[PDB]
Amino acid sequence: DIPREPRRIVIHRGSTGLGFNIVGGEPGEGIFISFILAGGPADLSGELRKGDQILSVNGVDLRNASHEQAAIALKNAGQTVTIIAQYKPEEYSRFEA
Image (cartoon, rainbow, N blue to C red):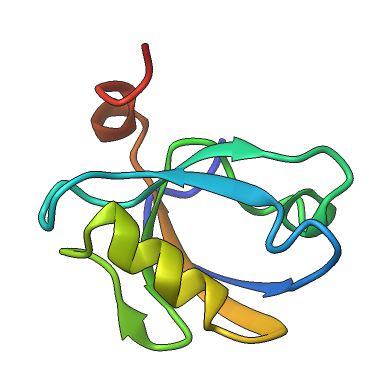
């Protein structure tokens, strides 16, 4: 199974951006991966999972980021991005209808 400790992942921005969607809310609710595009930069890696919490991007802490703050940071992270992710499906589940 997938590790539950934080994991360092590197994504190369492409035509589809980073190739995943995030869900979140107000600061403190957390930033979670809600969708990964097949064949996109985040699938290619085989490392990221729906339900991963994004703890940081290129050293920018996103633990208490709002959805809007995380979206900005991800878009301004550049062409190559270091994501530190931690698999948290139980916390992610509350966002998924």
